[PDB]
DNA sequence: GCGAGACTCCGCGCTGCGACGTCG
DNA sequence: CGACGTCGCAGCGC
């Protein structure tokens, strides 16, 4: 009763006994064995109980030649795909990557109900460290840790069998993993039921992982010439900014040096020094009204960020898609977050700057709009669809607090953020530009989620006591919100956690800390996690339900990764392809024929993802790029 | 294995560059 | 003195 690896493809009789038993199993685990040569799948291990790992070789030599590779590929797809009336669950460590490797390297599209123990670990504690196979075995199967004691890829985030960079055979890594993750996932399912989170796991979180796998196979379209065009414009503005700045300072300085900037502004120019000599964005936002140089430093930092942190990473990661005839970006989704919202890495498409303006040329300069999102384009002939939850966290705060004033501002009032800048600056709400509106937006959510008066004063260019009047006024105006905050802190001090709309718990032991810094931090986390975490739940429910509806149409492809395998073994592009998620907004790449059908499916499924005491307002915008979106009435 | 400090008081998140160190 | 290295910040996003 140790690791028994059964090489099922070594004897044709043993293989048909294996296929027979496999087709009876309602639950099993698989672990892809991948080696270098490379995304070479040399086989997979299946486990449906105990310490038996049935290794299905997809390569060798000791295999029965009567089992051709194409024969073995037929049985592999037959056992990994459903008949749509039989419920069958597959346990897969790192399901997203395995799903993509199976499709792209083996031509097999998984068609069952999936369970990733990594996702289960996050669901039970969202602040836990990102799980590794070692951590899951250390936690749940500590007796089995010797099996991995030799394995050193175990403490990595990547699946054991998927880690081709290992001196161990893929057969042994996959076999070990299949047994460990099968029994671990059984423990994790008992914990999910104990916490009443298994329906969230099976109906929301795992299907959410399925949608992100389609997104990662799709990628997002990217125009290299559009991005290169903006870099030249920006770099010319940067050269002019540096020239004008050095004339104002009377000498050359380093924009990247906080000391040179502090010396010029305060030591030389004698600008109000404000514990001081700080070159922060808050300090320069106030000083830019007195002298032009602070504003030039802010513009220099904005453009340098766009060039060094956006332009070059995007052109670094662009890949050619020969089937669509375009370049695309393929980011990696990340769902192990504190509040359950999805982010992206390599590169982080969510960080693409909003549109900004640069004046160039003589005589005050003519305006030019830098829209880096305009570089993200659909496939030739398609459109980008952008449906957005209007004021999601504010409507969730209204549903949970029943604050009649907030509900009134949402249903009838004008834009809150523009009205905040108006009362702040004593100006018209229409005169508020996007930069000022963004300042008022952070002021809004900052005050709501517990910002102090010292920081609010540094953000508003006023002193701490005048900012305290703004905070005190908000509490006076919005007592329903303030009582929801008092009640949330109280219930978190009693329970040790807070809950989202779906029941997910975030544990905040600092709520009972005596140090006032740690206590207040947990108190603000408690209020924010409930709202932001519930917003993340709703967007996930909508993403899953939209994908379920798009696949009811036979013309639809699951992803570009699927269709480009069906072109390799006469497919006009159809349907909408999930390309990006923006915390309260979903982007889709849709064919022109189905631009209206997908737009109606997206809006209706978003507006009815959950039922709240406040309606979920959704606005759909379609355009020829992420940056050139126009309203679409749907 | 404990929990200094006076350091830390909107929340969530990713990453290229700069500041200070190191090998040679 | 230079190349290469490492960790955290401060820039941007929601
Ligand atoms: C609808 N009526 C006609 C009322 C009319 O709009 C009056 N205003 C204007 C803004 N505003 C408001 C609204 C909300 C939200 F709707 F989201 F609940 C939140 C804040 C918050 F959080 F920023 F304080 C708000 O700002 C404030 O209340 N103050 C005191 C404030 C103003 C400016 C500033 F720079 C800092 C604070 C509000 O009620
Ligand atoms: N705590 C906090 N949450 C923020 C902040 N900025 C954004 N968020 C969260 C709450 C709202 C959510 C989405 O914000 P967006 O800016 O995309 O949307 P919005 O705030 O409703 O404005 P708009 O409709 O103009 O996009 O992200 C911030 O500064 N602090
Ligand atoms: Mg929004």
Image: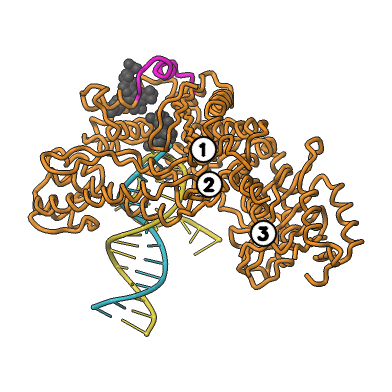
Chain colours: A orange, B yellow, C cyan
- How far across and how far down the image is residue A45, in percent? 76, 59
Answer yes or no: are tags 3 and 1 on the same subunit.
Answer: yes
Q: Of discs 3 and 1, which sits in the foreground?
A: 1
Find out whether residue A495 is within the magenta segment. no
The quarter of the rendered structure image containing the N terminus of chain A is bottom right
Q: Residue at x 72, y 49 (%)?
A: A91
Q: Which residue has dot 3 on it? A: A138
Query: If you read the primary sequence from the N terminus, does the residue marked by circle 2 or circle 1 appear first?
Result: 2
Q: Which mark is residue A254?
A: none
- Give the mark, 2 or 3, whose residue is nearer the N terminus: 3
Q: Chain of mark 1?
A: A
Callout 1: SS: strand
Q: Earlier in the sequence, mark 3 or mark 1?
A: 3
Q: Position of residue A150 (x, y in %)?
A: 68, 71
Residues beneath discs 2 and 1 located on the same chain: yes
Where on the picture, by quarter, is residue A366? top left
Query: In the rendered view, does C9 fall on the left or right side of A167?
Result: left
Dot 3 lies on which element? helix
The one of A480 and A47 positioned closer to us in this rendering: A47
The quarter holding residue A63 reads bottom right
Judge from the rendering whether residue A238 lies leftward or rightward of residue A322; answer left or right. left
Labelled disc at residue A589: 1
The reply to whether the C-beta atoms of the residues labelled 3 and 1 are less than 8 Å apart is: no
Magenta-tinted stretch:
A401-416
Query: Marks 2/3: CA distance?
Result: 45 Å
Q: Main secondary structure of the magenta part?
A: helix
Of circles 2 and 1, the one toward us is 2
For the point 65% across and 51% down, the residue is A568
Whether the magenta-drawn stretch holds residue A414 is answered as: yes
Q: Which mark is residue A324?
A: 2
- From the viewer's side, name the closer residue of A388 and A402: A388
């Amino acid at each position: 009763e140790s690791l028994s690896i059964i090489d099922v493809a070594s004897d044709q009789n043993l293989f048909q006994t294996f296929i027979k038993e496999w087709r009876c199993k309602k639950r099993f685990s698989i672990s892809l064995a991948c080696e270098k040569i490379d995304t070479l799948v040399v086989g997979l291990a299946v486990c449906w109980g105990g310490r038996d790992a049935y290794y299905f070789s997809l390569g060798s030599g000791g295999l029965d030649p009567s089992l051709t590779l194409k024969d073995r590929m037929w049985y592999l797809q037959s056992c990994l795909r459903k008949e749509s009336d039989k419920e069958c669950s597959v346990v897969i460590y790192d399901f997203i990557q395995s799903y993509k490797i199976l499709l792209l390297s083996c031509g097999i599209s998984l068609e069952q109900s999936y369970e990733d123990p990594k996702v289960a670990c996050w669901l039970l504690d969202p602040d836990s460290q990102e799980p590794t196979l070692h951590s899951i075995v250390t936690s749940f199967l500590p007796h089995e840790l010797p099996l991995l004691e030799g394995m050193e890829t175990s403490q990595g985030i990547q699946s054991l069998g998927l880690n081709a960079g290992s001196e161990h055979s893929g057969r042994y890594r996959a076999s070990v993993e299949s047994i460990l993750i099968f029994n671990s996932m059984n423990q994790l399912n008992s914990l999910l039921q104990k916490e009443n989170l298994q329906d969230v796991f099976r109906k929301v979180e795992m299907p959410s992982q399925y949608c992100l796998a389609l997104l990662e196979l799709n990628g997002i379209g990217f125009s290299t010439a559009e991005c290169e065009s903006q870099k030249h414009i920006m770099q010319a503005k940067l050269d002019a900014i540096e020239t004008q700045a050095y004339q104002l300072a009377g000498h050359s300085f380093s924009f990247t040096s906080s000391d040179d900037i502090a010396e010029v502004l305060f030591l030389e120019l004698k600008l109000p020094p404000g514990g001081q000599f700080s070159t922060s964005k808050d300090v320069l936002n106030k000083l830019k009204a007195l002298h032009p140089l602070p504003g030039l430093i802010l513009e220099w930092r904005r453009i340098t960020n766009a060039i060094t942190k956006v332009v070059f990473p995007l052109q670094r990661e662009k890949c050619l898609n020969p089937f669509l005839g375009m370049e695309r970006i393929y980011p990696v989704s990340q769902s192990h977050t504190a509040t359950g919202r999805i982010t992206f890495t390599e590169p982080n498409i969510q960080n693409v700057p909003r549109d900004f303006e640069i004046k160039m040329g003589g005589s005050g300069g003519m305006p030019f709009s830098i829209s880096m999102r305009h570089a993200f384009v659909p496939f030739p002939g398609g459109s980008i669809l952008a449906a957005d939850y209007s004021q999601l966290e504010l409507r969730i705060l209204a549903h949970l607090s029943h604050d009649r004033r907030l509900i009134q501002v949402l249903n009838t009032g004008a834009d809150v953020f523009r009205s905040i800048a108006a009362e702040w600056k004593m100006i018209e709400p229409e005169s508020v530009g996007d930069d000022l509106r963004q300042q008022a937006k952070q002021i809004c959510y900052g005050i709501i989620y517990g910002m102090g008066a010292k920081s609010l004063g540094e953000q508003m260019g006023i002193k701490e006591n005048d900012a305290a009047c703004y905070i005190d006024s908000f509490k006076s105006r919005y007592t329903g919100i303030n009582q929801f905050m008092t009640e949330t802190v109280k219930n978190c001090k009693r329970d040790g956690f807070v809950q989202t709309i779906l029941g997910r718990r975030r544990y905040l032991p600092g709520i009972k800390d005596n140090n006032p810094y740690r206590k207040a931090h947990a108190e603000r986390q408690a209020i924010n996690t409930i709202v932001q975490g519930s917003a993340a739940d709703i967007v996930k429910i909508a993403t899953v339900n939209i994908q379920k509806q798009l696949e009811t149409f036979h013309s639809t492809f699951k992803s570009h990764g699927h269709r480009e395998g069906m072109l390799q073994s006469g497919c006009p592009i159809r349907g909408g392809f999930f390309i990006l998620q923006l915390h309260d907004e979903l982007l889709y790449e849709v064919a022109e024929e189905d631009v209206v059908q997908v737009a109606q499916i997206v809006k209706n499924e978003m507006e009815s993802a959950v039922k709240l005491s406040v309606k979920l307002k959704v606005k759909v915008k379609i355009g020829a790029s992420w940056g050139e979106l126009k309203d679409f009435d749907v």
